[PDB]
Image 1 (cartoon, rainbow, N blue to C red):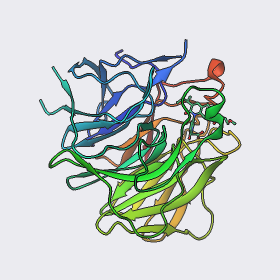
Image 2 (image 1 turned 120 degrees about the vertical axis):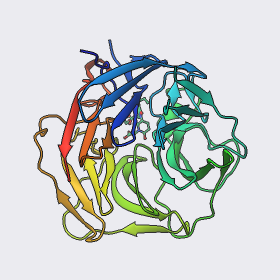
Image 3 (image 1 turned 90 degrees about the vertical axis):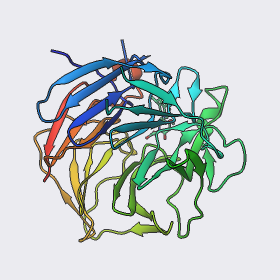
Image 4 (image 1 turned 135 degrees about the vertical axis):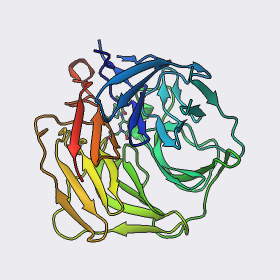
Length: 326
Ligand SMILES: CC[C@@H](C)c1cc2c(n(-c3ccc(=O)n(CC(=O)O)c3)c1=O)CN(C(=O)OCCOC)CC2
């Protein structure tokens, strides 16, 4: 049967019925073919591979993508020659053609492993890992000292918020109030209404357990302190909105390098986490993707079952894990 190869660090976006999968890498390391676009039909469980043309982005891991009215947008990532800040569009409504957009304004620094919130005409990007910004811009950047000893170009984490306005394809940075979360990468973002949630991620020697939201109307940051038991700190997890009041969390990697198979729901109205029982306790995943379907399910694809930092033993997956959340 038509089935995409195993991979981690790919993107997966959806319209609630079809899930589009692109990029990523695997071992036996190499990037998956840049021209392939895999489409999973969430209702039938079948895959279809299509070959794209146009301004095909380079093969990358850690890119950040969205699907808005069946138009896919892709930002950033890491290819064979490093990080990028290029922005692409792929209209999937109707051979599919990638379009690299010449954006106006100052783009974000080249980076990967970030997150995005969609709010009306705006794509709002947050955080990531990559090069030192070419100029001192709004926000903070912290170097990863380990990147000076094993590479020609040092990298670090940022807490930057950038808006790509789809009305004009212009980059800008909002002036925020409140305490932004620390710089981080491999955090997870989820949007509900005008609230852009962000949970966890890596910063310095920690994989974090903090939860915040940015008000996408006022640009005010808020820290959420749920009472009672909270999930363990992690990076490379997924956080997916499943209703107007619930975010679904799955997998990830702890500070002490444990791959995770726990799942939880964060109830926004109660400001509480509820652990979610599921049949995949023996299928931990990190750097997988998750997409919510119109039928209340969360579809998880790819990612790695163990510590992918030991490249020769990494267990990249091509499994679809289906969570019946709502
Ligand atoms: C994109 C290539 C990928 C396989 C990759 C490889 C390596 C690293 N990151 C990174 C870089 C930044 C970052 O925030 N995270 C997320 C996270 O750590 O949760 C992973 C990669 O993303 C970071 N490293 C690392 O953590 O080494 C262990 C500690 O060393 C004292 C060193 C090898």
